[PDB]
Picture (tube, rainbow over the protein chains, first blue to last red):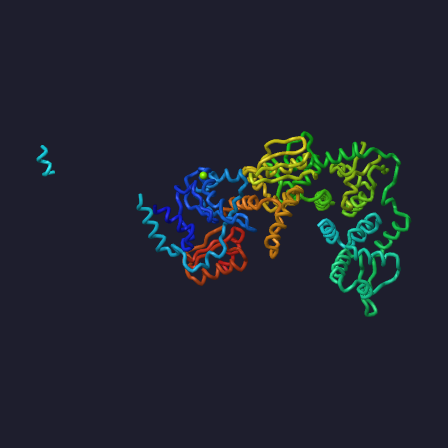
Length: 142
Length: 445
Ligand SMILES: [Mg+2]
């Protein structure tokens, strides 16, 4: 019941323009209004999950207006095992024909007023927080 | 940079030696052709008239629009000393070199030529069957040796010595092998005309004590000769050079008469496609080429997988790119080869992509990229991976008694451009090994 209300609000209520899906919404949920797509975490090397997640924005409402181009961002940590999983879980889309654009720098990111964990104090606090994660009558008696 | 490279060499020649180079009309006819069109116009005017013309008269000929060209033409003409500036009676008179003037007049007027163009025996031979195959194979044999692909016959020591002594095809005895360098890949990229000049230009510099003038009288005279014709026998130094030129696939000898080759005439002036290939997002290569040259060059930075009679198919891999990069090939050169050797189908779709990009938003003119942008980025990214670790050699300076001394020595290194790192808080800095001696000497003084 709660998720249906959330989905309807996001679909028809302009206030909720962004949501945070999970593995449950990885496939078979139709969002005709979705145009942009982002992914933070991943289920290791599965190339199928990559295609299913992309499908949420492939059925956007305005898929015929001039110059329409949906966006799919894949944030991945450099020098980690994520590159092994990223290049391994995106080998199917390349076969289809999709081409990923490498974004080494995002223009205008520094001029945003406030950014989370901008100071070392917050980074240290977060580091410790995440690190610490790991006789039927007798019945009356009783 | 064809004429520029040849012209640059001619400038370093002393004026006393340049005068001797103008004695033979054969060389003059070629040196006349290399100048800019405007320069050639003025030279032809002064050659036949025995008078002195002020430079102001020359300026009158050129329109205001072509004033800039008149500066390059006069500068280039004066650099070669072909135009002699004489100042007298308050006017900067202009005259041509008498030897160059006389040499040009003799050739154009059909006068005595001192056999600068050679002689004819009338013993023509078949060129396509033998000359084309011989020189193409001989020029291909050196390329296969350059590319590193196996081939039974190896080039003679004369050219091999030149290659090692030249920056081209760096070699090491300890390694026991020959590999191409950054300029070597550029050499392979240059057209046949420039591809021949580079080896010849290196040959000009290699030769020492064979006179410098004699070598030029022969090379320039070679272009004058016409393929498929006989020429009797020439200078003594030219005889060994003629045999030397036979090793470069320039002149063919039956064993009294020498026959120039197609490459000889190609040296003077210039003159689906073979070598065209398609690049997919899967890093696959499909070359519509049937020729060892295209196949051999592609294998430098491509992991070939299979081939057909009409086309060759392969796949780009990190290992193949890493092997190419280890040889000194820059990613910019690789993309240039792909862009300049793109299939027409890629160009047409790429043109459509530009048209579509401009059709949607004609305000901006995005660059015409034939191949998908991802390939360029990934290739550049692979280059960044090799440049990840950066290491220098030198000495670290520390334990400074006073900050002033630390700043003085560190500032001195920065001035001479040998400082690599410094830290005011720790009073330490690092300098390159090259500047170590200079810094130490300054420290003592
Ligand atoms: Mg379904």
